Image (tube, grey):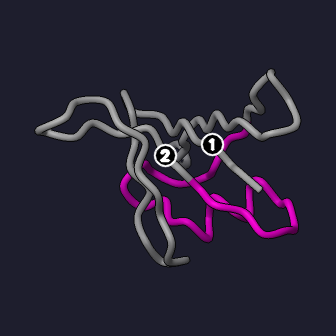
């Protein structure tokens, strides 16, 4: 009966070292607004997520809408947060 959880790694322009945070939701249910809340960083950002495209393989996909579902990579989320 354990609560849902997704491991989230994200890179910012400032740091060469990525940040690690956990979101209390199942991958597939996690939305951009969930991700933004975990990051909790004000400013004008773009958000790219590591994803598997069926034609091109590993890609970075951008997500715009707050209610939009975040793609995962090997059951986790790997993200780039760019100012």
Q: Name the residue at 47% across, 64% down.
A: 63
The quadrant the C terminus occupies is bottom right
**Marks 2 and 1 close (CB-CB < 8 Å):** yes
Residue 26: % across, % down: 45, 51
- Classify residue 32 by image quadrant: bottom right
Separation of residues labelled 2 and 1 (CA atoms): 6 Å
Report the front residue among 64 and 32.
64
- Classify residue 18 by image quadrant: top right
Mark 1 highlights which residue? 80
State how many labels appear.
2
Q: Let me know if residue 38 is in the magenta part.
A: yes
The local secondary structure at tag 2 comes to strand
Residues in magenta, as a range: 21-47
Report the front residue among 20 and 59.
59
Residue 4: % across, % down: 51, 48
Q: Earlier in the sequence, mark 2 or mark 1?
A: 2
Q: Name the residue at 85% across, 68% down.
A: 43
Mark 1 crowd level (few <14, some 14–19, many ≥20, 10 Å Cα): many
Above or below, comparing residue 10 to residue 69 in the picture: above
Q: Name the residue at 11% across, 38% down.
A: 55
Residue sticking out furthest to the left: 55
Q: Let me know if residue 40 is in the magenta part.
A: yes
Q: Is residue 2 left or right of residue 75?
A: right
The local secondary structure at tag 1 comes to strand
Mark 2 crowd level (few <14, some 14–19, many ≥20, 10 Å Cα): many
Mark 2 highlights which residue? 49
- Classify residue 47 by image quadrant: bottom right
Q: Is residue 33 left or right of residue 1?
A: right
Residue 44: % across, % down: 78, 69
Report the front residue among 62 and 32.
62
Above or below, comparing residue 18 to residue 80 in the picture: above
């Amino acid at each position: 009966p354990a609560a849902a959880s997704t491991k989230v790694l994200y890179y910012t322009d400032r740091s060469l070292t990525p940040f690690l945070v956990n979101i209390p939701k199942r991958l597939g249910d996690v939305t951009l607004q969930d991700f933004k809340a975990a990051v909790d960083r004000h400013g004008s950002f773009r958000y790219h997520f590591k994803s598997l495209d069926p034609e091109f393989g590993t890609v970075k996909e951008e997500v715009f809408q707050d209610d939009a579902v975040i793609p995962g990579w090997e059951g986790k989320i790997v993200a780039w947060v760019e100012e």
